[PDB]
Image (spheres, rainbow, N blue to C red):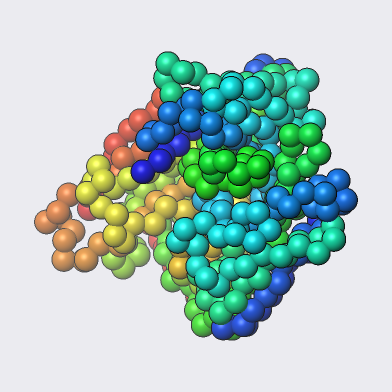
Amino acid sequence: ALTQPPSVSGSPGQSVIISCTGTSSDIGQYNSVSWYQQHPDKAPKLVIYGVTSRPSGVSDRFSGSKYGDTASLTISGLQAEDEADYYCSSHADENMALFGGGTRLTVLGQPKASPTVTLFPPSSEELQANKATLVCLISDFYPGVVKVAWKADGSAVNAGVETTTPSKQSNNKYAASSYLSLTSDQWKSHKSYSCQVTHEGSTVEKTVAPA
Amino acid sequence: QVQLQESGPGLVKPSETLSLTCAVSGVSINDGYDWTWIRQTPGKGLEWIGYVFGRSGNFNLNPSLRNRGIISKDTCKNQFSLNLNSATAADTAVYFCARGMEGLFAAYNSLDVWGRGLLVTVSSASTKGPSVFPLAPSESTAALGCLVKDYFPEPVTVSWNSGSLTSGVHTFPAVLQSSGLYSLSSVVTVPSSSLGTQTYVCNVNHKPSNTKVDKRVEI
């Protein structure tokens, strides 16, 4: 591949240089480089084409350069709207193109927020098949790391559990979810279950019980 | 407008062929546009696969995938296609189609229009359709939801009241179980006075199994 730094960070209103280092037979030999912006779960957006040019409607805040076998993107006037993975690509010898390994741009100093936790019991439609699950949904939080644990009758549960790696929403805050998977006897065994989520040392807890 | 959209099987078995089409709107497939395929192995970065030159029908691929696939253009349907033989687990990725903007040298490097992407999964496993259950309030304050259990492969798509709802809807990323089957959940935040005054239903579609279903969150 072309080589990029795995991640880079910058404060609001600042400017950042994102770099892609290839070899002489791709970045060097040809004045054909481009940059793409990718928000998660969405298609890449073209940001610069050739070493220098911008598509229509791409903001004046983006510019491109090349020196020797290396090329770079400048983003200036950082908004949180600029938080994305950024990919470089260049034409390569005899009718190819090559991508760089990608780089994740973190825009620092955004307002923190602790999770809007929601919790639901098994459906009565579900436990009629004598299998039962608890659904805990974790929404609108930043920064994006969470500790999360379940309890049965106020005591900790360490089997039958799965939890997502967190995911960025449209609004740059994070979502996640946790699931507890039970038989109907194991649902009925306990008069309440709780999902406990801890974010920046502050704790949100949500509680559920039969009927 | 110029629009592209991917089509193809969501599941492929090891050492089959994986095929995809990209249907082109608003421009002729013959307009000379470097009709390009790109993949993104999930959370592992972009790969360029290759292109078709619209007005000559010549094609070229990535030196890993030439000698194993072709790309072609269909003049009758106004679309282009990737055929990628001897499929392996590594070929599991989101596949995108794209347009190289007109008349650049190496325009397949400078891709102005992109398609939505289609996840293709390579597995010896079987497709399995979802089990769909409603989630209903008293026990979370204003949110309805739905649960979509133990399906394969990815993805499943969800909507509320047949697309009458968009505001206040949020569908969560799935989680992989140890069984290799996935599950996910969807919610909609409802103005609490509306419960039983307005009907709430979720539409669900796991197309790799042809499973389309609708479910009543019956208050």
Could you say where residue A47 lies in the image, as x and y percent from the top left? 57, 58
Which one is in front, A130 or B171? B171
Q: Quadrant of the rendered structure where residue A130 is?
A: top left
In this view, which residue lies farthest toward the right? A24
Q: Where is residue B127 shown, x and y percent of the image?
A: 54, 25
Residue at left offset 58%, top offset 34%: B34
Look at the image and tell me whether residue B181 can be seen: no
Which quarter of the rendering shows the N terminus of chain B? top left
Whether residue B200 is visible here, answered yes or no, is yes
Please state the total of marks drawn on the protein image. 0
x and y, in percent, of residue A115 in the image? 48, 72
Q: Position of residue A206 (x, y in %)?
A: 45, 69
Q: Residue at x 55, y 60 (%)?
A: A54
In this rendering, position of residue B31 left or right of residue B38: left
Residue visible at 28% across and 65% down in the picture: B142
Q: Is residue A79 above or below residue B103?
A: below
- Name the image quarter holding residue A143: bottom right
| Vertical order, B106 against A202 (above or below) | above
- Give me the residue at 83% from left, 53% from top: A28
Horizontal side, residue A92 vs residue B37: left or right: right
- Work out whether B86 lies above or below B99: above
| Closest to the observer, B192 or B55 | B55
Front residue of B107/A11: it is B107
Which of the two residues, B4 or A161, is positioned nearer the viewer here?
A: B4
Q: Is residue B17 above or below residue B184?
A: above
Left or right of residue B112, residue B137 in this image: left
